[PDB]
Image: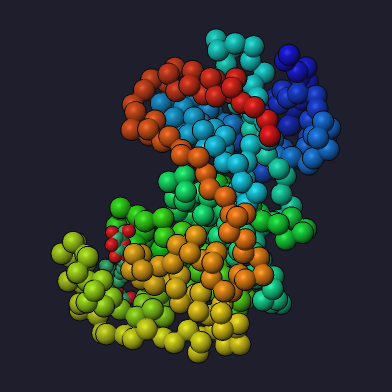
Amino acid sequence: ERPTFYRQELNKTIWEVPERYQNLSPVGSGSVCAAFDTKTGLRVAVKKLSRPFQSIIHAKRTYRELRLLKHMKHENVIGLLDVFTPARSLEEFNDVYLVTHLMGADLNQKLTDDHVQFLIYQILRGLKYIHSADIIHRDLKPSNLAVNEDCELKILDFATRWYRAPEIMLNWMHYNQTVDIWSVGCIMAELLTGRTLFPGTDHIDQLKLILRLVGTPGAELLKKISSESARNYIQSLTQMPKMNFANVFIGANPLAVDLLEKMLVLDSDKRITAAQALAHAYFAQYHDPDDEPVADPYDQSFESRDLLIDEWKSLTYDEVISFVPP
Ligand SMILES: CCCCCCCCO[C@@H]1O[C@H](CO)[C@@H](O)[C@H](O)[C@H]1O
Ligand SMILES: CCCCCCCCO[C@@H]1O[C@H](CO)[C@@H](O)[C@H](O)[C@H]1O
């Protein structure tokens, strides 16, 4: 059966939610309220989408977000606890609310090596799963990594470009999933040193900092560059050698440094993958190959479709109705 809702007034909006969700307090601005799910005993975030069907693009984005959240079923990836609408029918369907775990903190005095191992391990475990679904995150950074008290980590979907892969800043397109491994390297570096690895003031400054660490592109990488203007600029640069990372990450676990060398490679084809990284000896204490699950195939065929608002809205409604809680 359908739950009983109650109506409230906060975030300048009316919130109509099932009564299981109690003591809503605004937390951010769609807008989010913290709540207590009386059914499960969990603290949750309830997000009321703003303007979900205002236009074709908003409607497709709303669908996109719901299909994504519904697919993600992994300990280290945010998942969907509930989705609801106060609407009794498609004709009434105007609002969408998404319920997830309420996380206390994000990753944004030094962490111990054991602790850095555990955090990066969980990132990589989550990323193996996301990548197995043929999804690329593209914006992994400390504000998209939630942690609880137990140091248990989840990757979030959610201006900083300090963790962005160099190919993205050069507008490459054709991105590999290993864009996300570059970002993991930057995050890991900062957990080890307590400072931003590549704190650029603009994208050129950032690229300059990257090249100083990893060196200018070698002939092997140049062979794969089709952009004539890019090639021309690159070969005009003073040749800089790759720094030895041990002399940059002083005192870090040698295994950490080794792993960083494998993540922070300019050529995206030569970067370690998430699945490979989980088997690296830095993670020996956490790695369990029978407990690093992969995702069912994720149908992103809708991305190639151009539909009407009402069609995206009906598809979304179908997804609300068919939701089954975890
Ligand atoms: C891959 C394409 C990158 C284009 C960036 C080109 C210019 C950025 O390079 C900048 O310009 C000046 C020299 O031109 C110098 O003062 C600086 O070293 C540099 O900050
Ligand atoms: C001066 C800064 C240059 C940055 C060079 C980045 C090279 C990135 O790596 C590349 O990325 C592509 C997209 O996945 C692939 O198609 C290539 O095979 C690969 O070489």
| Residue in the foreground of this view, choosing between 98 and 257 | 257
Where in the figure is residue 42, as x and y percent of width and height? 79, 40
Residue at the spot x=51%, y=74% of the render?
259
Residue at the spot x=33%, y=86% of the render?
241
Furthest toward the front, the residue is: 290
280 on left or right of 284: left
Where in the figure is residue 229, as x and y percent of width and height? 18, 65
| Rendered-image quarter of ligand 1 | bottom left
Residue at the spot x=67%, y=18% of the render?
86
Residue at the spot x=36%, y=65% of the render?
268
Where is 35 relative to 131, above or below?
A: above
308 on left or right of 38: left
Where in the figure is residue 246, as x and y percent of width and height? 51, 87
Residue 144 in view (yes/no): no
Where is 132 relative to 162, above or below?
A: above
| Residue in the foreground of this view, choosing between 12 and 274 | 274
Residue 257 in view (yes/no): yes
Quarter of the picture holding the N terminus: top right
Where is 202 relative to 69, above or below?
A: below
Where is 164 relative to 81, above or below?
A: below
294 on left or right of 24: left
315 on left or right of 282: left
Indicate the colouring scheme.
rainbow
Where in the figure is residue 66, as x and y percent of width and height? 54, 32
The total number of labels drawn is 0
Quarter of the picture holding the C terminus: top right
